[PDB]
Image (cartoon, chains in turn blue, cyan):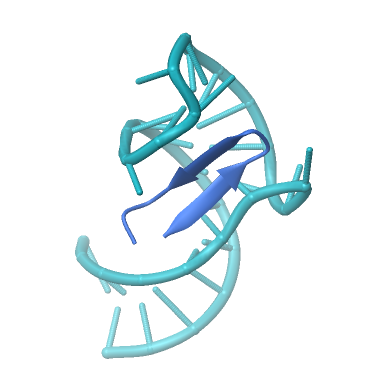
Length: 14
RNA sequence: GGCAGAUCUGAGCCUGGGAGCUCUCUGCC
């Protein structure tokens, strides 16, 4: 999974 | 208990600014 944090672009494995 | 999805947004933190830490919501078994 992919996720963004108003600045920091993150992700969780798939 | 396990699995899946989610952040100019569901929120905060760390600097390296990610594929890290914590919380929350929804769905399924």
